Length: 154
Length: 150
Ligand SMILES: c1ccc(-c2nsc(N3CCCNCC3)n2)cc1
Ligand SMILES: c1ccc(-c2nsc(N3CCCNCC3)n2)cc1
Ligand SMILES: [Cl-]
Ligand SMILES: [Cl-]
Ligand SMILES: [Cl-]
Ligand SMILES: [Cl-]
Image (cartoon, rainbow over all chains, first blue to last red; front, side, top):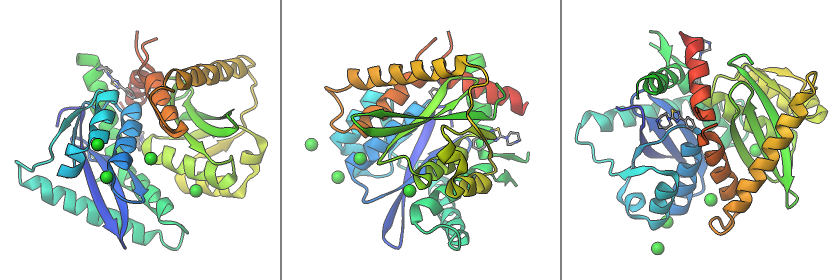
């Protein structure tokens, strides 16, 4: 849970594909609906994330994106260390499962509001990142605190 | 500028449209290529920005987006105060002009690398936010908002 470490997570809703990056130390996320989880989609998503936050390491969500030359090229371009996402600490899988369930619940709670899934996913990213836990600091507050504490030391 | 204030900027390249949000105090940006600058696209862009960073106020880039009920609805949903983008300080026009020129120069420098403009714009966002000016814009926005939290 160093300041630069993120995890990719791909979840499905009604067969549409939601790709999520979770900053491990804070639980802050960014997410997008994508047409299918291809190398090309994941690479582009990682390029966006790393221009916006200081992404040092990413634990990839599966072996296809770990292997993908397109994902490796974007990781090289953006100075990201690509790593596997094997849950050596088994509590990792349950934390990700619980986030996906939370995200899907919020999506459901905004269905009277968003015509397209992509809006509902961004409403969910907003409510996730601003939720005070359960501190009570939010994930958005913690990621900024963590990275700023890192700049002032290293 | 206060830690929550952002400015929208829309620039064109090839007749494709690039929409940029600039965090005024730091110069950090996020940007997207969009098919045309509609209320719906601007609104969606603001909803994404405000889920990622604490967006208190946005200076909108033109009167159409200031007026748009779709943009006002996103601003209401995301708790953003919508403001005009009138350069009461005329040096603002120039700072945004220069950033657009710098963004387009980076886009040009990555032509041998990105097949699609959308990739080039995100490589430009990356190089802009990491460039040491010596802190980078990315460092400054985190510093600014963290000072505000504490
Ligand atoms: C995503 C990323 C960062 C944030 C975020 N940073 S500071 C902050 N707060 C500032 C102090 C209380 N006022 C509003 C909350 N919130 C929120 C979502
Ligand atoms: C977008 C948003 C934030 C950043 C960002 N924050 S801290 C950081 N570091 C840059 C160099 C490595 N360690 C010193 C601090 N860089 C970069 C781009
Ligand atoms: Cl693929
Ligand atoms: Cl793509
Ligand atoms: Cl290949
Ligand atoms: Cl849209």
